[PDB]
Image (tube, rainbow over all chains, first blue to last red; front, side, top):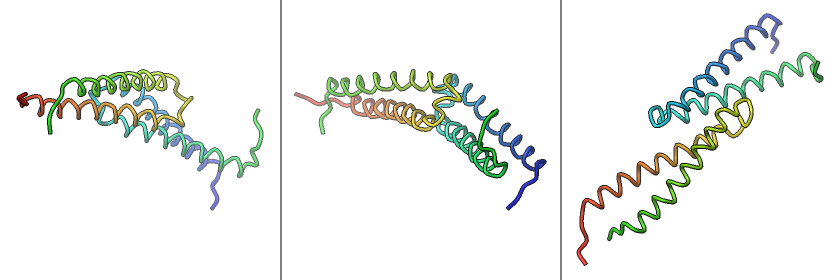
Length: 71
Length: 71
């Protein structure tokens, strides 16, 4: 259980794009109401999960970096 | 088994007002993004359930009101 800085960046980048894409598509889906209403909970879950997993990465990399403070 | 449009109307009324409240709440949350993200799945479920219940009543009331109780 160890990841390098390259793996970290690529992984974070992947997660960032993952969360951002879903978040943007959800914003559009909110306007696509009773059209894509059957898909509401999908993107809602995905956006929540993506950002929760993003946080899961943040909390894990924090302990790794000894990252306990901000800039 | 007897259909009464008035109490059904009150039922629909209560659902309409509820769905309307949930719709604006969801809309607010959608623009209030990277905030309230922890409540995304909750609110989204409400709106979906409300819509699904609106559709439900609409299908149910149509099947019933397409008949006629004599009194």
